[PDB]
Amino acid sequence: IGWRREGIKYRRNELFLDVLESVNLLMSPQGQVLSAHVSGRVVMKSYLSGMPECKFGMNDKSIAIDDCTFHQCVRLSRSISFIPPDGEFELMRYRTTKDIILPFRVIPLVREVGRTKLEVKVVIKSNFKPSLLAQKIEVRIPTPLNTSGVQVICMKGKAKYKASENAIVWKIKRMAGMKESQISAEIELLPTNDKKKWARPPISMNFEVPFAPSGLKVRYLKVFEPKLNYSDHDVIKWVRYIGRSGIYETRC
Amino acid sequence: PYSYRHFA
């Protein structure tokens, strides 16, 4: 054990777990999931007295881990067991493909108006308990290269056309679960090469949500240190979940 | 405004 020294003491014996997940999505214009995965890692900040034997239980088998490396200190068998380094370390990393919660449903609607205008409506639906708030929601609607200007209306958030980037960027500070927001935009088209079909790229999203999209949920983290005279009941334990978009594209 | 909750 060259990852933890031997004489370690704390009045307040406390640990913190961060479940950090990136959820990736490619949805067809109809609503098929073409492809979707989650990449996750658990980080553990530990301030525990001695050299303790901890047992990390999640809800495996309940969700389905495709595969997952671990950290040195993990003894493989069959639940997860270790003597943690002190302070902060990555306990595990993992991937998931099955039974993924997709926190956001993006519903695009596009209408051509002769050769002068594109009419676009986009609806976002949040798909999770009303009690929880997504934050840092960024919707990105791409615009053709022949774009003279853009009008947008939206009741929630602020949106501005970014011509440098050829996209409308709609930002919402926070949104509750089980809700709907929409944006309307009118895109004014310069005339163009006549035989140029717009390769309509995907509408894409950014968000942070306070839960694991994988479905992963921490059930216990048990601390046993048999020398010293603090039991498990004495340890103060915290989780937080931070699920963030990776690639989260919906085809229009 | 939150960050960090007890399990269950």
Image (cartoon, rainbow, N blue to C red):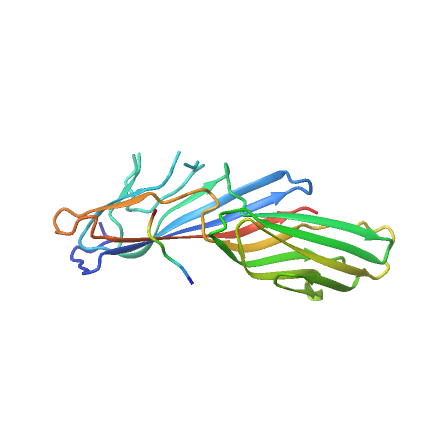
Q: Residue A139: name its quadrant.
A: bottom right
x and y, in percent, of residue A54 in the image: 25, 45
Residue at 47%, 53% in the rendered image: A132
x and y, in percent, of residue A195 in the image: 86, 50
Residue at 71%, 57% in the rendered image: A184
Would you say A62 lies left or right of A118 here?
A: left
Q: Please indicate, yes or no, whether residue A247 appears anywhere in the rendered image.
A: yes
x and y, in percent, of residue A178 in the image: 55, 48
Would you say A118 lies left or right of A2 here?
A: right
> Which of A174 and A252 lies nearest the eye of the viewer?
A174
x and y, in percent, of residue A238 in the image: 32, 53
Q: Number of numbered discs present? A: 0
Would you say A190 lies left or right of A33 here?
A: right
Residue at 56%, 58% in the rendered image: A137
Q: Is residue A97 above or below residue A169?
A: above
Q: Residue A219: name its quadrant.
A: top left
Residue at 77%, 59% in the rendered image: A186
> Which of A123 and A131 lies nearest the eye of the viewer?
A131
Q: Please indicate, yes or no, whether residue A199 appears anywhere in the rendered image.
A: no
